[PDB]
Amino acid sequence: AFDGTWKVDRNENYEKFMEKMGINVVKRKLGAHDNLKLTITQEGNKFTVKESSNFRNIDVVFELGVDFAYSLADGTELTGTWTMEGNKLVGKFKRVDNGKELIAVQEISGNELIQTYTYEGVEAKRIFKKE
Ligand SMILES: CCCCCCCC/C=C\CCCCCCCC(=O)O
């Protein structure tokens, strides 16, 4: 599964996705080189993710199928759920400020972890390698 420590390797269309989200030019450069590392552990229906990046170090804890709130590094708040569909984690979120939907899918491709995000018609992906 997703268990383990994962470190971001490369991105696809990420700066354009950040621009749509409204992140300023300089911040997008920083975002794209965030050194993000995720440590994922599961305990039944619940996941604990240690998110560690140049921006912050926080714990993200959620139960599959239960809504929870999550804040983006820039302060943007989302609420939504993650559910396991097949072998992927599908996340359906909504920004609290403007009510717009933000979808995220997480899947394993060989030995890489791929996250894909969609927002307002733009897609982005972040690919992680296992440490
Ligand atoms: C200044 C830097 C701005 C960074 C903007 C980030 C863009 C949006 C990213 C992804 C939203 C993913 C929502 C997932 C909730 C936590 C679950 C998980 O990551 O496994």
Image (cartoon, rainbow, N blue to C red):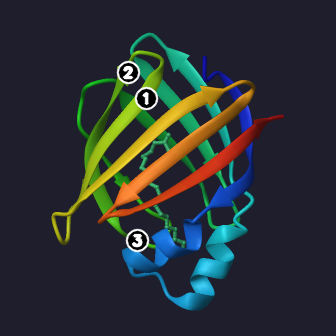
Where 105 falls versus 40 (above or below)?
below
Q: Position of residue 42 (x, y in %)?
A: 53, 18
Question: Residue at 43% of width from left, 29% of height from top?
Answer: 89
Task: Look at the picture and state if 114 lies above or below 126.
Answer: above
Identify the disc placed on residue 75.
3
> In the rendered image, which quarter is residue 112 located in?
top right
Q: Earlier in the sequence, mark 2 or mark 1?
A: 2
Left or right placement of residue 25 versus residue 98 in this view:
right
- The residue sitting at 38% across, 21% down in the picture is 84
Residue occupying the far bottom of the picture: 25
Mark 2 and 1 residues: CB-CB less than 8 Å, in contact? Answer: yes
Q: Residues within 10 Å of mark 3 (few under 14, many from 20)?
A: few
Label 1's element?
Answer: strand
Dot placed on the residue nearer the N-terminal end, 3 or 2: 3
Q: Where is mark 2, residue-wise?
A: 84
Quadrant assignment, res 104: top left
Q: Which residue is mark 1?
A: 89
Few, some or many residues within 10 Å of mark 2 (<14, 14–19, 20+): some
